Image: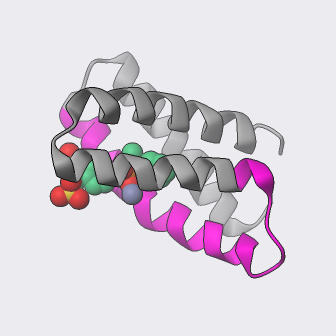
Amino acid sequence: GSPLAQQIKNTLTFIGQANAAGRMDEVRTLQQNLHPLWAEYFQQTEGSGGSPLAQQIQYGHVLIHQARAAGRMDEVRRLSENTLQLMKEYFQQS
Ligand SMILES: C[C@@H](c1ccccc1)P(=O)(O)Oc1ccc2c(CS(=O)(=O)O)cc(=O)oc2c1
Ligand SMILES: [Zn+2]
């Protein structure tokens, strides 16, 4: 894949590994690492006409930022879980 796609894949794997161990501080760090990588990747795909599965992920990503900033902690938890799963499945299409 692209180098950026591999960076995202690796970072998703790390988030899953941290989640498995219950290391919530490391999950937070790794989600923050994912943030700029996904943002850049997504806009690259948009510059070449777009992917509906990518668009779906990004829609959820925006909703997550809106929920988190508003303190809507239940909506953040649900949306993060579902969107990170959509991204794992997307990048498993390799
Ligand atoms: C889950 C990630 C994602 C990444 C790509 C797609 C879908 C979800 P994300 O939403 O981008 O990851 C974050 C970002 C920021 C924070 C903050 C800091 S602030 O902006 O809230 O001040 C704090 C925090 O606890 O977690 C974050 C997670
Ligand atoms: Zn983000």
Residue 29 visible? The answer is no
| Residue 33 location (% of width, % of height) | 38, 57
| Residue 83 location (% of width, % of height) | 53, 37
Q: Residue furthest bottom?
A: 47
64 or 6, which lies in front?
64
59 or 30, which lies in front?
59
Quadrant of image for the N terminus? bottom right
Q: Quadrant of ligand 2?
A: bottom left
Image position of 5 with respect to 68: above or below: below
Residue range (magenta): 25-54
Q: How is the image coloured?
A: one colour
Residue 49 visible? The answer is yes
Is 90 a magenta residue? no
Image position of 77 with respect to 51: above or below: above
- Left/right of residue 68 with respect to residue 46 in the rendered view: left
Q: In the picture, residue 20 is in which quadrant?
A: top left
